[PDB]
Amino acid sequence: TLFRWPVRVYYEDTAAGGVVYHASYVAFYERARTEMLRHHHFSQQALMAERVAFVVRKMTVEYYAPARLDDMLEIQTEITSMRGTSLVFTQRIVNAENTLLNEAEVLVVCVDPLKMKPRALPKSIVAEF
Amino acid sequence: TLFRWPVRVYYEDTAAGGVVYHASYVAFYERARTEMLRHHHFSQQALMAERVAFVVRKMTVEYYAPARLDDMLEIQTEITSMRGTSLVFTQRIVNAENTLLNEAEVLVVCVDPLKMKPRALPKSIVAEF
Amino acid sequence: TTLFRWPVRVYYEDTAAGGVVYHASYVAFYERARTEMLRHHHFSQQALMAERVAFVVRKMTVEYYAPARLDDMLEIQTEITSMRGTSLVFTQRIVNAENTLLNEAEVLVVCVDPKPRALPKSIVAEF
Amino acid sequence: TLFRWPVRVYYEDTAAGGVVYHASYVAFYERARTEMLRHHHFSQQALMAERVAFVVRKMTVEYYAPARLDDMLEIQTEITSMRGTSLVFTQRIVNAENTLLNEAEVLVVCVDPLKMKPRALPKSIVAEFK
Ligand SMILES: CCCCCC(=O)SCCNC(=O)CCNC(=O)[C@H](O)C(C)(C)COP(=O)(O)OP(=O)(O)OC[C@H]1O[C@@H](n2cnc3c(N)ncnc32)[C@H](O)[C@@H]1OP(=O)(O)O
């Protein structure tokens, strides 16, 4: 089920061309994943209490049009796949005119932050999604 | 042919998990492509002179193992495909023990800096690579 | 008075390997708050673009009293405490959810032509 | 006893105004302090494992002139005070033509990172910087 997250573009996100730096979008996507989990009570507390961390294993981003300084964006996020130890997030960013700026597909793996090796998906997360 | 670029990991690149933040690698890869171009005399000055800029159209990043604070990394970069308006860079990151940490494939489009619309690769770029 | 409040959530991108917010991240947080304060007083950046005005930091002093951490919801507090000629001073501080004072800053900002120009009369009148 | 460190300005460091973002200089200064420690044989990743870390307690930065894309900068760094738990770094940034761009003064405090509580500077670090 879709989760929406608003993001304002600030000077820090821009680059010399007047557009958002392409790596800043990657950070925006991470914020939206974090907020989606937070919304489902999967805070860092609840995660690291039942043995977890989440790390990015593979990420594909396709860039169509730029965001500019002071734009108000919407990050849209869905969990489209769940396996043994991993989830796939399907994400995209639109601007206030609903113009599609870029899209991402993010494979995420559940690990142990001390040693960082694949841990099975907690059943709480599987049932929640 | 392979272009090698060293990158040191600083606090600004790390996050609270104690490893490099996944978006930081995207910036590392960009620096290596910039320095690869610079090695062939395609500086920012030479590119502006021939009315050319490069933008990332699509990027896939594979995260195998973490970099940490104080690691001296080597980014390895090769141009593996050259189309009419487009270049594909294949890149990878190893640490000082030559452990493969990370790999990327980057589709880069040639645009004019005025309209940001695609344009044919400069003949010098085609001839050089 | 001019006191403006702005919330900021701490994300992974803001943290560093020590487990706390990287010290340069606070500098960005303070800039967002100045930007939003100006938006609240009807000086969005596209409006400022139309009046030929930009703002650049000339000098800043930051005091780091206690750290912010991943997932903290912070409040940036911002006041314009002086204005004269071409420049103005922002006084800013950051508190966490317990109202612990984490940080404070004094920022000298100069109005420029996107070179130093006098403050707009509307900006001075507003503050 | 100055320590010099070069830094190339990349597209990631620029902002919409065409110049380096004012917070990027702050990161440049941190890199130079880290490299000064590294030149004197100290690794902050290794020190972390010994429950030793350094945090910024106070910083002043003055911006005189901008850096731009592809500039090769030199960060210049000295330790000007050292006592108890703390060090003062005095730093500046010049460009390739030796134009003074930026200056900073940074009060740094040694802490146990587990508790984020100050501690005496390591004896070997004191020995190293006089
Ligand atoms: C390590 C990874 C990061 C790498 C480098 C970075 O980016 S560094 C990240 C940015 N820097 C920081 O986060 C440092 C934050 N500062 C601190 O944690 C602490 O100030 C610190 C141990 C240096 C110093 O603590 P001290 O109390 O011994 O020093 P000092 O007396 O000067 O502190 C001034 C005021 O701050 C208060 N104070 C100190 N620690 C506090 C805390 N944890 N929670 C609430 N208040 C605190 C003091 O009691 C005092 O309050 P009163 O004046 O009201 O009596």
Image (cartoon, coloured by chain):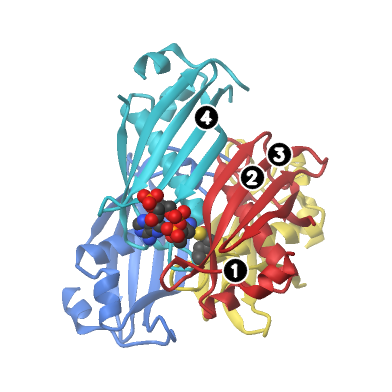
Chain colours: A blue, B yellow, C cyan, D red
Name the image quarter holding the C terminus of chain A. Answer: bottom left
Marks 4 and 2: in contact by CB < 8 Å? no
**Where, by quadrant of the figure, is residue B1 drawn?**
bottom right
Query: What is the number of the mark on residue D121?
Result: 1
Chain of the residue where label 2 is placed in the rendered structure: D
Indicate which label's residue lies in the foreground, 2 or 1.
1
The answer to whether residue C115 of the structure is visible from this angle is yes
Asked whether the residues under the numbered discs 3 and 4 touch, taking CB atoms below 8 Å apart as contact, a structural biologist would say no
Which circle's residue, 2 or 1, is located before the other in the chain?
Answer: 2
Label 1 lies in what chain? Answer: D
Residue C67 location in percent, x, y? 41, 58
Residue A122 position, x and y percent, is 24, 83
Q: Nearer the viewer, mark 3 or mark 1?
A: 1
Question: Is there CB contact under 8 Å for labels 2 and 3?
Answer: no
Q: Which residue is mark 3?
A: D101
Label 1, residues with CA under 10 Å away: few <14, some 14-19, many ≥20: many
Q: CA distance from mark 3 to mark 1?
A: 31 Å
Q: Secondary structure at mark 3?
A: strand
In terms of sequence position, does the residue under pointer 3 or pointer 1 come before the other? 3
- The residue labelled by disc 4 is C109
Amino acid at the residue labelled 4: Val
Find disc 2 in the rendering and name its residue.
D104
Kind of residue sitting beneath label 2 = Ala
